[PDB]
Amino acid sequence: EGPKTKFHALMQEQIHNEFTAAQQYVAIAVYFDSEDLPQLAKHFYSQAVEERNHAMMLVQHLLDRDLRVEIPGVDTVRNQFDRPREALALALDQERTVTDQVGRLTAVARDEGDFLGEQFMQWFLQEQIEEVALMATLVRVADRAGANLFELENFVAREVDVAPAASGAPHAAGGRL
Amino acid sequence: EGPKTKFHALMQEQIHNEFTAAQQYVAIAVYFDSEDLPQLAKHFYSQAVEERNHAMMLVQHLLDRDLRVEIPGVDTVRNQFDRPREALALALDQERTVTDQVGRLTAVARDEGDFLGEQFMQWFLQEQIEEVALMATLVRVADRAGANLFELENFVAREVDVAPAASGAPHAAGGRL
Amino acid sequence: EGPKTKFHALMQEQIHNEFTAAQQYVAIAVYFDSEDLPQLAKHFYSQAVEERNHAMMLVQHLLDRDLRVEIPGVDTVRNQFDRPREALALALDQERTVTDQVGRLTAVARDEGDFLGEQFMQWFLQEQIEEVALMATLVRVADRAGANLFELENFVAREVDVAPAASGAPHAAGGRL
Amino acid sequence: EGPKTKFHALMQEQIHNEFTAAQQYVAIAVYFDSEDLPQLAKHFYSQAVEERNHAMMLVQHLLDRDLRVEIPGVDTVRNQFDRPREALALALDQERTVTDQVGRLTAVARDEGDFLGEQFMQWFLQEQIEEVALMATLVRVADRAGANLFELENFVAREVDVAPAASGAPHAAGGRL
Amino acid sequence: EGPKTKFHALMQEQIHNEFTAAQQYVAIAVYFDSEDLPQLAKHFYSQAVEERNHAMMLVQHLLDRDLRVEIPGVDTVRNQFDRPREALALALDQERTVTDQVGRLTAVARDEGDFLGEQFMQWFLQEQIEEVALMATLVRVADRAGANLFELENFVAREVDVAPAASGAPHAAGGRL
Amino acid sequence: EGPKTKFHALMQEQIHNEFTAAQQYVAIAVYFDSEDLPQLAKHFYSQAVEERNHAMMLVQHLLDRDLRVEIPGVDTVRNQFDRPREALALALDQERTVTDQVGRLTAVARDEGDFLGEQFMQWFLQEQIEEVALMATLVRVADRAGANLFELENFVAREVDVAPAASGAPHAAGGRL
């Protein structure tokens, strides 16, 4: 079918990962919406869109370099959470994983001398900094709040804002949402 | 875990279906984008968003009636197409299926006397009319064009427009995109 | 030539009916215009347009579901009226008939499990409520006025208004007039 | 019932003709809309309105001179066409007929010394010039295009425009649409 | 006095119910206003208006179909509540009842082939979805808050908003308030 | 349960009265709307709102002085009227009663040295002047018109206007409508 370099072969895997991550954010947000925490839910509904946009960016990068790309299925994501702290912890966990994955991609790109591939994912590293920062902040605030969830709610409302996205963001397939 | 009526149990299945349908639209659009048919691709990138919005509407309806709802995984969708006519045919097929599914939901709702459920899906029937209409039109135009794909391209560009959505649309979880 | 379901076969008949109804409204309006009752005439010239729009909506619905549709002829409509009360009574009569016809369509659609067809005609039921209301009001006012027609004229002028059409109206073939 | 001059008696016939012509334009437009030629359809949906307006103008002229006028039925119009060239040819044919009919009216008016009647139909002659011109142009373009219908489509889109109607148009009963 | 169908006879009962429901909302709001919970009170003063508007809509529907309609008295409503949780629970209860009542109306309409009546109350079903959703949310939030009522107060202030009413709402007798 | 002064005990009764009066205005307006007198109906739909606002003002006054207040039921109001003159006479009657009731309140307040209570109801006396004036005017005009109801209709349309409410109006519970 044609010789795949492992940057290509692993970036396909990453497309799959970002899609599953988006679905997981939707599930987290839906759990928050059922438990009557609408600011938390709002934030995570925004994050799901952001993650889908990341997936589209990866897809668009494959389309640009004319490598074959599959739009894959998504694995079953988690829906049961006993308290909000666990769902937030899951988000934080996921984002640390995503960071390590993007690290793994940059490394494999640099090994096999794929300079376009090296360069493309600097933006993903940049986004991971701020993203893991925000998640860690939310998890720590959720621990300080404890069972009193309204204070978590107020913290998300006043201090966490999804500001307009800056430039430097690569093109996403079908337009950035 | 609690007694599920089969309207609830089948609407969960429909949530799963709409999510898979959205992913299938993304795959179709990505195939069109690789084959350098960007108006076709643009339309289908819009349709994927529309289908995700439908899924969110179903989810939001479950959240409103306080029934448990799972955000599910997505099955593997199709990526190989030998010519554009087949991908368009797949879209048309999918939408006829979706129509029959929504029909099945309205029927099961009316059987078990779920009046909120009966009423909720009239909007989905309405959307299916225009949607299957548009798909059928595209498939017939793709047959008239044959191998000369630029005329299909021009038809999509001039005549097929994604106009502003009208009201009557129920609330989608996390805001309609 | 192909298997017709009786929803399709009866909706064709309804297209014929709405066209004849529009021509009948034109005839009524022309009688009112000859007898120097221009507010009455104005209202009915508006109603004829509304009825033609309904016919176009039915036609457009057939075009969308890709069923064959004939644009039919129109039967001879009534022109002789001895007094205005009779022409108004004819209008009222016609609209009660139209209501029963649309009822018959909803019933036949629901019998043969045509869910798109069931759903499409809810708007027609809605329109019939307000329409028969208005006609009944005009007939009762025409009885209170008796031979003194100027008071009927003033009632039509001040109180009966053709307000901007609301949304929810399905698409009419060749644009709503 | 009263002595009819044959200008009056033939103008009634013309009212009938213009109504049938309008219904025939609707049928042509509906055939074009089913065969996915929406620019052609758009033009003919506009022409049907124009023809109804002509009928209303004739009606209004009868109302002004206080002669009795019947709003008649419409004969069955044609719906089957094997290719677009034939429907266009039918339109062209119809308009040549209409021209000859209006000629016949001007002649009969001038015979029986009906000076108001002579004068009223100069506008109809004027409209027939441009109208038959446009139809002939469309038929010739449809022949140059042959089976490749998209070029016909583009010609209708770019070059054929329904510009704002000029003055000189007599009053139509119930307002010009 | 004339033959009443039981759709008519039960819709009269529903008019009575909506009036009593409005008075009950006023009583709930007045209890909240005495206990110094003004955001809660504000919301319920808005809900009382909404319920009166529903009553007016039902009345207007009877007026349109020219059936006799009584504007009835209202039963004694509840004023004593020992804590806010109970008044909220009463509201939730009431709205679940209203949902079942509107269900009963749709069912009786569909039994006796009253297609206008079937169609009229789809809007009421739609409103009940969102309304019971909101009430359930408030009751669950009131349980999470417990005796600390200020957090309930803040939740009502930030997250619960009476947005502009959408279209699709039928006409209310004497104008929607 | 606590010592009630009879100003408080009679003002509760007045709250009940104003609520019943509002429902009676709704019934009168609905009778006028069924008999096709929409200007009359419009006026009385406005008066019902005004009466509900008065009830809310009384309620708000009880809430301000921290006395217990019941939101009561409403008695059955009158719906049968043989002619419009009687419904207007009923309105006039009601308003004369309301005037006497408010007089009785001012008197009882002044007896028991409730200076806040004395002062609060001066506005109600002021409103009763203009209100009974308007009702008397309508009844006299209805007598001059006799069976010819259109002239009554025109008088209500041109001369009776619900102007913007002036200041001096005390606060109504849940905002003045």
Image: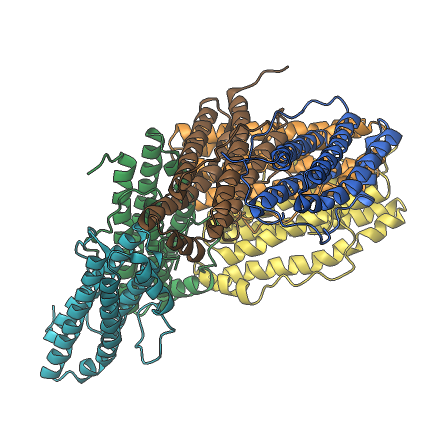
Chain colours: A blue, B brown, C green, D cyan, E orange, F yellow
Quadrant in the picture for residue C160: bottom left
Up-down: is F119 above or below D159? above
Count how many numbered circles sit on residues in the image: 0
Q: Is residue E44 visible?
A: no
Up-down: is D60 above or below B134? below
Quadrant in the picture for residue B172: top right
Residue A172: x and y, percent? 61, 47
Nearer to us in this view, D104 or E71: D104
Split into 4 quadrants, where in the image is the N terminus of chain D? bottom left
Residue A115: x and y, percent? 68, 46
Q: Which residue is rendered at x = 78% and y = 51% of the image? A: F171
Residue F60: x and y, percent? 79, 45
Nearer to us in this view, E152 or E87: E152
Up-down: is F122 above or below E125? below
B68 lies left or right of C141: right
C145 lies left or right of E146: left
Residue B103: x and y, percent? 42, 31
Quadrant in the picture for residue A14: top right
Q: Which residue is rendered at x = 73% and y = 37% of the image? A: A107
E57 lies left or right of A167: left
Split into 4 quadrants, where in the image is the C terminus of chain D? bottom left
Q: Is residue D151 visible?
A: yes
Nearer to us in this view, A73 or B92: A73
A85 lies left or right of D1: right
